[PDB]
Image (spheres, coloured by chain):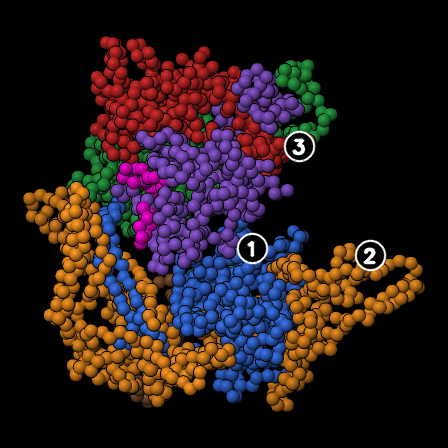
Chain colours: A cyan, B blue, C purple, D red, E orange, F brown, G green
Amino acid sequence: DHGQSDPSRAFAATANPWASQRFSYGDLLYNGAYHLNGASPVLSPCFKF
Amino acid sequence: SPVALHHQLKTGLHPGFGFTVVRQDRFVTENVLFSERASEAYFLGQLQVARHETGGGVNFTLTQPRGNVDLGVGYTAVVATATVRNPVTDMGNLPQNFYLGRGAPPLLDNAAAVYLRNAVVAGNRLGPAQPVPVFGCAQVPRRAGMDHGQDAVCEFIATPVSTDVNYFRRPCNPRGRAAGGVYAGDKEGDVTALMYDHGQSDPSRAFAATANPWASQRFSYGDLLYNGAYHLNGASPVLSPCFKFFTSADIAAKHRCLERLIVETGSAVSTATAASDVQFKRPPGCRELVEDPCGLFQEAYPLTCASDPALLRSARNGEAHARETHFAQYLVYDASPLKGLAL
Amino acid sequence: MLADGFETDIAIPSGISRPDAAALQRCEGRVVFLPTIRRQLTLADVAHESFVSGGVSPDTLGLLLAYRRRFPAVITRVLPTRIVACPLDVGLTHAGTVNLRNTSPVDLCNGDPISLVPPVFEGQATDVRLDSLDLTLRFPVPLPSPLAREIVARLVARGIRDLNDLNVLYYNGSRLSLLADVQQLGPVNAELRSLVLNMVYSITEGTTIILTLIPRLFALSAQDGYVNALLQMQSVTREAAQLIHPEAPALMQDGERRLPLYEALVAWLTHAGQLGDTLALAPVVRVCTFDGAAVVRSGDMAPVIRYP
Amino acid sequence: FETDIAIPSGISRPDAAALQRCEGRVVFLPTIRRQLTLADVAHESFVSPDTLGLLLAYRRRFPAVITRVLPTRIVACPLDVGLTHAGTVNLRNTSPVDLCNGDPISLVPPVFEDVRLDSLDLTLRFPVPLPSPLAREIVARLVARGIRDLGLPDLNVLYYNGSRLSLLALGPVNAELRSLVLNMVYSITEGTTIILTLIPRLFALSAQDGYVNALLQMQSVTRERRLPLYEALVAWLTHAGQLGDTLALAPVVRVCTFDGAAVVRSGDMAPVIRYP
Amino acid sequence: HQPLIARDGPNYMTKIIDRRALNAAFSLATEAIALLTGEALDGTGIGAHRQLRAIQQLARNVQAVLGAFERGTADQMLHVLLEKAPPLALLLPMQRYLDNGRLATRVARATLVAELKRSFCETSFFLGKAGHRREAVEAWLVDLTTATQPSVAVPRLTHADTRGRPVDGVLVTTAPIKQRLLQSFLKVEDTEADVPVTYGEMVLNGANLVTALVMGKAVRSLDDVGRHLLEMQEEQLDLNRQTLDELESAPQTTRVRADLVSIGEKLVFLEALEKRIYAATNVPYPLVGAMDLTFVLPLGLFNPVMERFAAHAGDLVPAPGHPDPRAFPPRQLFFWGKDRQVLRLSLEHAIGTVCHPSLMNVDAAVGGLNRDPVEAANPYGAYVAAPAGPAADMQQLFLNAWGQRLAHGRVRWVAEGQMTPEQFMQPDNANLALELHPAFDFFVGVADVELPGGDVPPAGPGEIQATWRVVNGNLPLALCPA
Amino acid sequence: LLPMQRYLDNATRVARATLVAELKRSFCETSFFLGKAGHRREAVEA
Amino acid sequence: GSPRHHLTRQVILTDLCQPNADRAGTLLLALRHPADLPHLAHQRAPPGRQTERLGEAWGQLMEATALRAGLVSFNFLVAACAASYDARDAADAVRAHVTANYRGTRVGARLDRFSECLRAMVHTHVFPHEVMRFFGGLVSWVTQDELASVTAVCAGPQEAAHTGHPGRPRSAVILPACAFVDLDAELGLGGPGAAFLYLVFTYRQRRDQELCCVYVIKSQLPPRGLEPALERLFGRLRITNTIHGTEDMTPPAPNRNPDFPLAGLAANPQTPRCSAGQVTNPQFADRLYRWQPDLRGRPTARTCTYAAFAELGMMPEDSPRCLHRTERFGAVSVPVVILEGVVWRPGEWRACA
């Protein structure tokens, strides 16, 4: 939700428009729910983020 | 103009103003007591059994009335503040709306009064979700989550540019003139003569009558925004931190005995709550026994503050190595009771 | 007991002077507004200090709107350490009889429903002020109901004037007037909305038949001494009959199966007959004097048993 | 607690039989009192009043249901102070309406269809214990009849508990109910013109298009010679506020049946409580 | 007795008993009553066993409430001794002031404030600021035990050691402070103390009341009211001769395990009370207090004349061929947050205080500055004339009619041009009180004159008017300098 | 743990939010102790 | 001390309510005799709605329970209106044991039928707050073929009435967690005080898209001051009823009524008038002003109702205690709100028009 502010830094809605919002460039690459990179065995460290 | 001053504060133009931000913080402490060989007589009574009935079953409320006798000629007990736990409030930047408030005459053009409100409330941490009802308080929208603690509500008092910064490098009054009932003498009208007579000089800095003509004098711009006497912001639950600095009816009501004002600011009643979300005016029931140094002196304290990120970093070394000023820049190093705590 | 009675304990503080302590014992049968149904409260909750809004102490009309958001209770015995009350919404007592006291200049009779009214009258604004505690106790005035619908009508219709005399009443031939004061614009608009909603909702398709009876009332007023004493000297329908000749629409949609007047009267009873409860509060209370006298004088107690 | 209504002496043989029949029936006393004469009970004490005069009088007086009837005195208990102490007092139908379980029961003056004692020279009118959702109907049907005299065949047809009521069964009840009709019509014709003078537009607006958008503003909270108009406001709020009490017919009686039939028919007795 | 000392050259203490009451509940259930009374009983073993589930439900509730009053004593004594006690940061001035003179000169009161301010900001949190030292801390605990005057009452039984030395004080700390003080700063000298057990009783000499019915009116039958006085006043001696003989014979003192630390010249109970009393109850431990500190942050100020410099010639230099973003007037603030944040506070946060249209609410100021009748000033700028005649003779109408008006007193706004911004806020001028708003000029005008009209205004009095400052340039040069 | 034992003795929304500022700070300071401040003694014995 | 209460007994057909599946301590709501339903629909309906719908929808229910002023248990009523709540995860759990524990064949064909009855009630405009009447909470029952003997507390505290089984004699008020809506937590009232319990229906008037919801609301507000709190929750339903509840009523297109001229007619002394005997004569009434008001298709108050409440009882505690447990109804685990110590007081209904 980006009508609300970031609970860490409360004076901005986020720190990345390309990673934080839904259907962003960050979401499309590193979600389990879309499965881009679950076929390769190499770990993606931001999978839990 | 409140339309014309919107177009500049967004697009990066500095107008001829300067604001002095005032906010309030609450620090959980760890006190230390001391008492004496017989510092208080203490009386207890006889228990009473009161029977009440309820669909769940019969209640037995038990009462025992008790008594306190303070037989100390002089002072027999001491609180001592030892350490500092978490600060409750996050030392942040929560700007204050007056669109939460109610009781100000709108500008007459309904095409333009709606335009300003949709330009400031829309996308704000604080502005009302629903339009303000005619009775009761407007509500602050619920944040989905918090990380640091509650949000210290900032303020903006309009002050002129050409005041010196040296009035702020010392524990001072944000009004620009030293208020307070401690300073007065033994006449009938001395307390109002302190805060508003500007033929005399400031008791704190005696070579000038004020530091702010826009906030110290009667009917100033500072008084019209923040008073208990005029009720501009009587409707919002959000606390204004300079409410206890400007409301002249409350300073004039306190007494002058320093034997009792020192004890009564050991357990004074705060004007804020900790169970709130942002920071609220207190409900009429709750009482948080919080010691007030600002209650006695009507003075506020400076922070470690600058106006460059480059120039702030000289202050993390200590005190004598921090450069204070640059060509048009300045530092304010703190003079607080938090000077060597590394909080 | 739990069902029949409910005793609250309004606690009295420590430091009270005897000029203040001897004033509370004269407050035996009064009306006290609790905010809740707690069993332990303090005088700072009862008094006018807790009555204030955000900074604004409201006038006699806004004084109504924060009554009906609260709970009326009657003091039953003033002890030195506490005041014992009984909230009327729960239950009276085991015996179901609690003595009130007239503050009105008006006598009571048997079976009259009591509604309570603020201290509106002149020579009546009697606030028991406790100096050691800085507490005023604005006690309301138990009036009969056909007075309490007049005074609310005198106060609500007065604020409609100032959005662009009346203050003289008469009851049983005794002249009495109510105080006049400037009104806060806030609670007046909360009264106008409760009028116009319950007023417009009482208008139905069938009411255009009742409106055709206005020349029948006026032509009947010249023969019956009941209708002549009904209409008024300053009514509207007398001036509506001399200038307007209304007539009904001929047909109704699905006019076989529905009753046009029956839907008009039921909608009138549930919205405009209900209106006296939507401005003021409810007449919970009525007088049942047993053996003493059928008329209760001013300053005298009166036994009370609840009314629906 | 029980009151005693003493019969004055001089009772003939059918007159003791007529008072023997009113076992479970509602009686209005003026004030709660131990000693009480029968002449304050009877219809002589009400002077003859019409239906409006009874509805006023049935709120200033205090109802009481008769218990057992002694040959010397009538023992009755009031419904306000004497019923919260005792458990349950039986109540007899005089209505054509079957009582169901759990109904709230108000009282209606005897509009439909008179125990007269000839030796004592008095009559006795007794109210009709019918349920409160019908009480706001049966009054409202008959007032709607009298307006038509200054009908429709469905207006006299009432279905309750699968039973048909016929309000028609007409002559004297029309003249009996006249002061209601003269006050019901007037309080609406005065009502719907003062609105129509304060806000004069309300009929000129289009019904489903403009009038709705002007109705939503009335509903929302966030939006804030001389006609003797404002003296007619007060004139109307005291008269319409007067008919709100009298035609409320607020329920006294709630029936809770225990070890019996769920439906109490005409002529039978029904158990009654008024307190939890 | 007040201490008095003789000099060269030419009481009773009444204290109001505070009073509070306490509360605790007990609630039973519905089934719990039917078993204690006996209504749900049979002859079965199960019904006799079900009593034990409900009789002991009393015994688990009776102890948990009757024991909840001796832990109320420990609660209430904290909540009162917190209210008697002022903090150390405002006592080390006051004990030096009361012991010195107790003198009522306005100067000494005006030097206590310079003591109460400085001793607050320096010795607020001593164990956090200078807790790493040792010698400064061991003097701080002596500053606890010597800032208080020993009280009036001598108790009957006195707390002591196994040695029997009396204790003169009590420290109450939290748990982590007690662990820190018992490692390096203090010493435990004793473990088991002698403590009295009995409460104290009274000698009643009360005003007595006599109510007795008398059958008849005789001499001997009315003296029995008089005999009843000395019959009941004798019984008050029979009570009071017992209460002294009980306290002589009662078991007075027992042996109690509690920590005893000597500080300076006297013994002190050192005590932490969040494990005995406040354990597993929902009460805040009252010794964990709070602070209220208000802070000041200046957004958009400007440096004075002798402060516009750099500390070196090449201190903060931008890239060569680029403008220096430092010499511009600042509009921002940076400070530290709670979790080490480089926060930012600029003018665009001040929209919500200024864009709100109450900045142009002036009528509360115009209609009250004209309460006392202000005198008449020079109306050269307070007045606008309607134009007339040809334009060639327009100035000759001006100077020939305004000749004497231009020389009464000083023109206000021209004389404000030679003001140092430190001279403006001084009480030198008579125009402080007409500077109140950042956008409205407040001046002295002309009474009852609609504008524009007439060449010369009528000689009437003046009143304070209000005209909107249109642009940023209309601020005076003492509030935004050249 | 040491931030949590100081919380289980007082349950609002803000008092939960001040745990996280303590749970972050007490982790990043006192995660490893015999390697960071292992040369001192007074810090170790407490 | 033993408090005073009042019991009721009634021989009740077990088609709609089941005192075996619904255990001791649930709400019970009694009906009118269903011969009154198809005639009140014929009379109280607004113009242009199908009066022949209520008589057919109820007829399809009696022909579904065969494969008399009865009783509907609360758990049956919630699962019938289960397609209109917010917590749909628990609303499909209340239906899960209604179809699985109730004695009969195809209980799941009753719920889709009885809800079609309730949609016919709103549409044919006999509102079920004029039909559903409060009946007491369960304390015991006696079973039989096709009927049961139900014992309940019409007035009094729930925890005083003895159950009958000396192993577990008491009964607490058992409610599913879908209907129980607080107003203490959602408004912020955390202070102690006695709380009132209210039965609240909600409607939604559209053409063949109509709903029903039954709630039990605990509040510290009087019954005189509930209407500002119901409006805050259910104002979405209030807006949708004023513009969509008036449909197939024929409007006057365009407007025919002019403005009301009495403020202009009475000011001018030249306007023609009449005496008391001159009026109601056609030679003198035609000289006056003609005024034909048209009220047709207006959104009247009864066609704009969104909710209806009533008193139900109170909890005379200082701090009233609720619980949230998951009791097992046979083999189905259901979110249950358990009320503690309810003192029953019925009251009359009140529409929120």
Q: Amino acid at mark 2?
A: Gly
Report the disc number at residue D226.
Answer: 3
Q: Residue at image x 36%, y 73%?
A: E85
Q: Where D20 sits versus C4, above or below?
A: above
Q: Read off the residue under disc 2.
A: E453
Q: Quadrant of residue D57?
A: top left
Chain on which label 1 sits: B
CA distance for labels 2 and 3? 41 Å
For the question of whether residue E264 can be seen, the reply is yes
Q: Nearer the viewer, residue G310 or A48?
A: G310
Report the disc number at residue B102.
Answer: 1
Which image quarter is the C terminus of chain B in?
bottom left
Chain on which label 3 sits: D
For the image, the number of numbered tags is 3
Q: Amino acid at mark 1?
A: Arg
Q: Amino acid at mark 3?
A: Arg
Q: Position of residue E241 (x, y in %)?
A: 14, 65
**Front disc: 2 or 1:** 2
Magenta-highlighted residues? C77-100
Report the disc number at residue G94.
Answer: none
CA distance for labels 2 and 1? 40 Å
Q: Quadrant of residue B198?
A: bottom right
The secondary element bearing badge 2 is classed as loop
The secondary element bearing badge 1 is classed as loop
The secondary element bearing badge 3 is classed as loop
Q: Is C86 one of the magenta-colored residues?
A: yes
Q: Position of residue D91 (x, y in %)?
A: 28, 24
Q: Is B19 one of the magenta-colored residues?
A: no
